[PDB]
Length: 233
Length: 244
Image (cartoon, rainbow over all chains, first blue to last red; front, side, top):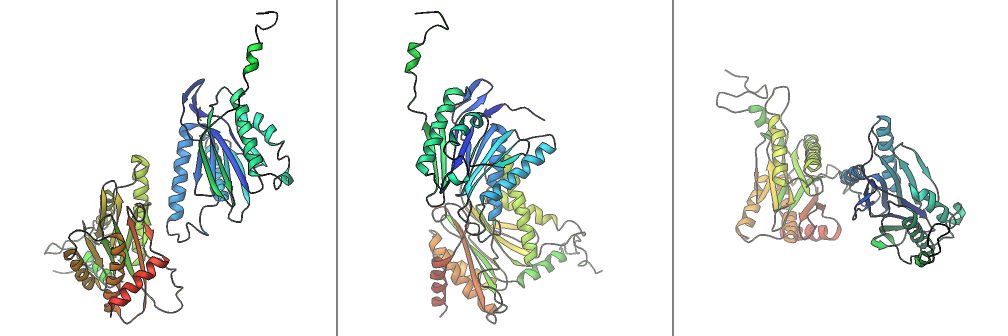
């Protein structure tokens, strides 16, 4: 049993007609001190999977190391490591899921909330969640922490049920995701303006975008607001 | 007296360890394999005897990768080779886990060296029935190595072991003389394809399948990779041509 120290906030994601999108800002908080600013919380595994991690950063780095090994190991005595026997998103997930639950079962959790985003070899989209309790679930949209409260409501307005997926495009989806990131920057006190976004499309493959920024921010109305009730000036 | 060759860690009157020597026999009795150090990497090649048409071609892969930058090939008791590679893999994983940086080839060699040497210390174990040629690229250069059942090993310019090791060593020495400046990755691959073909005469009776792999700073980015398709066929011909 432990307690998180350096932490990463929300990880949001959804699936559209051709793939999945996932994003996470680049902040590593230390309590209310916005300490680190170049933290990449999106871990690509191969070219069909991206693992988004929130929670304890030291634990995330550990999980990051476990993933590099998965790759190295899957390569051993595997002539089809980059073909039929390459790591599938489902394999990577089932693995992390296994670990997360074994660890909570030993009363020594990996203090994270994880979302595995990817496209299976048969083109199927993959999006599942697993946290420190070893709890797992899928849904057209998935977000951790704050994103669960603020991002999901927005993203679900785009893909409310399974059937809405084939009707959603990378443009519509990426747009939703980016607006969500702006909202989170507005109301989450543990968020950064800078973030990374990744797309895993069954055609264009994996597109990883770094150093994005929340733009188009409404603040002007703040000038017309003075006092907290009766104050006029 | 006698019997000095029945137990593994026993010194015979002349200071030898016969069991280790008998292991070397199993090695010589095996397929021929080689390694060629080039100007920025290394190439590994091996002879795969085709016992029959029933063996699926291109399948029973012999060369093995350790970590992501090391190649290993061996002649002798195959299962013993795998065992040693497994150990090397654990050996390499542990090193990277503590030091972060992938294991330097020299460091890796001593890991395999110490492990193999260890199996000549007790009579409760048998020495490894294989000689291994391995190497790769690291923080500073490419390195080629060969490890004997005794646990002995050195850095090589070129190395060979197995049935037709003599042919090979001869061919390798020629290259060493005729290229004091250093062969290239591309070149070594062909050269290797040839030397295996030549050395295959000491086994000309059975048909075989050639296998090559390389690790070049410029050709593979310092990552061990198998020579497949075109590059492979191109080298298979370069040999078939110079074998006549």
